[PDB]
Amino acid sequence: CPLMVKVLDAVRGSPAINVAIHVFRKAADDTWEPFASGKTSESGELHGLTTEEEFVEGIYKVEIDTKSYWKALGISPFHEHAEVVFTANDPRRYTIAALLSPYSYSTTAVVTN
Amino acid sequence: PLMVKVLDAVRGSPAINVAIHVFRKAADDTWEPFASGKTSESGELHGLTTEEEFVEGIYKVEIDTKSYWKALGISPFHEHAEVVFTANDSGPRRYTIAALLSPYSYSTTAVVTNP
Amino acid sequence: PLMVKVLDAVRGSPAINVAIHVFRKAADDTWEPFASGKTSESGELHGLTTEEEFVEGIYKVEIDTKSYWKALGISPFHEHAEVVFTANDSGPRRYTIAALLSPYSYSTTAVVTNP
Amino acid sequence: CPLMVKVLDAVRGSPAINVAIHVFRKAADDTWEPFASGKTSESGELHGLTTEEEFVEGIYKVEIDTKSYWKALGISPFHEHAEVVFTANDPRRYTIAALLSPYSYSTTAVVTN
Ligand SMILES: [Mg+2]
Ligand SMILES: [Mg+2]
Ligand SMILES: [Mg+2]
Ligand SMILES: [Mg+2]
């Protein structure tokens, strides 16, 4: 799979498990079309979102439902979600990593061949 | 009530001349333009709104990081950094949205204080 | 010439009353005490040193994050956050050391400006 | 192995390869005794630093030679290194992750069972 998402919890020092992830692809009329989705695993990872044949160049948005995650832990969060928006560019594998705190997050792209 | 501060993690400096657009979610669920501006030489953007106009709502702060890096000769990963949050739902607050930029990474933090 | 700013990423607030110790590497390669203080209600620590006393050297800023979290009922991962850097080796500069704290994570950024 | 170190490069969006890592354990006289060391792999990871039998409770310091890494890339860095200091506490595995930029770094502990 050319696109993987990994989420960590900076409060508990753990993978962020059961986080909902939605991927969108920008359409020609500038709307966001649903592309793929899932929930992070026990390791905080979401694999299998797409395939080399499907993941063509274009602008993609990855929406990480951080609010529901913090709500399930009983911790008041700031953001509605974390969104990562990027242009896929032709070999490359994309790992979108996110590090979550209730009032802060960071995201990093690890792009490898 | 709403300030944006942007730092450059490659140079260890404010990120100057960064375009910032703020949107507010409308009743029909679309993003309406709310305010815009660009960071100063200190990397801050002040004066976007007022206590009266900054009512409860869901707000989106779009920071044009890609143009910033491209003007410095770098092709970055992200199209922009987007910060989406509910504001003032417990009464008016002061919000500082901070962003720390690298070509393939950014972080964003909110500092929320009660006037 | 040297300021330290500390933010709490759990609460979205300045990190208040954080103890900070600064050390400078001596000629015998040991860490000598240089200055200390604690963050204010704004999460900043000003006045640690002066342009005259802040000579070239290798400096270490130790931020006592563990005591901060423990006083809030949290058992954090790190003993402290340590920021080590060469200062003023191209002439005097102004340094802001920023730290962003979570129980199992922190980040630190330097903003360096030329007077 | 109970202790793993992973390093990412936020400028290139890649693992940080060939980064020197030194681990120290605090001695009874408060000095730092060398404990283990190595260099990150092509995946930015350093495995095999210690064993369950050796990695007893105590205070450990992980020193990541960020300066030499940035110098080899030709980019002027701020820090001499990144140090992560923590008390190991009894099952647990420790992953020390670091995200490097020339004037900033973050470190996170992912502690799992
Ligand atoms: Mg092309
Ligand atoms: Mg209401
Ligand atoms: Mg000299
Ligand atoms: Mg015990």
Image (cartoon, coloured by chain):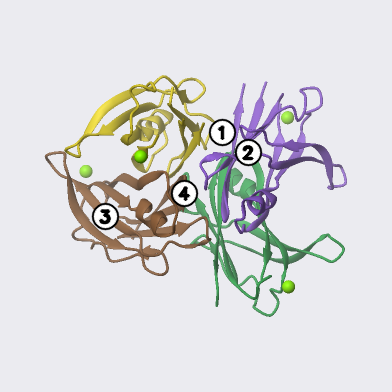
Chain colours: A yellow, B brown, C green, D purple
Amino acid type, callout 3:
His
- The span from disc 2 to disc 4 (Cα, nearest Å) is 29 Å
Q: Which one is in front in this view, the residue at disc 1 or the one at disc 4?
A: 4
- The span from disc 1 to disc 3 (Cα, nearest Å) is 34 Å
Q: Residue furthest bottom?
A: C52
Q: Is residue C25 left or right of residue C84?
A: right
As drawn, the label of residue B21 is: 3
For ligand 1, the image quadrant comes to top left
Q: Name the secondary structure under disc 3.
A: strand
Label 4 sits on residue: B103
Task: Report the front residue among D32 and A88.
Answer: A88
Write down the quadrant of residue C113 in the picture.
Answer: bottom right
User: Residue, x 50% and y 20% (percent of image)?
Assistant: A42
- Against B68, residue D18 (above or below) is above
Amino acid type, callout 2:
Phe
Contact between marks 1 and 2 (CB within 8 A): the answer is yes
- The span from disc 3 to disc 4 (Cα, nearest Å) is 20 Å
Residue D111 pos. (x, y %): 61, 29
Chain label for disc 2 = C
Q: Which one is in front in this view, the residue at disc 2 or the one at disc 4?
A: 4
- The span from disc 3 to disc 2 (Cα, nearest Å) is 37 Å
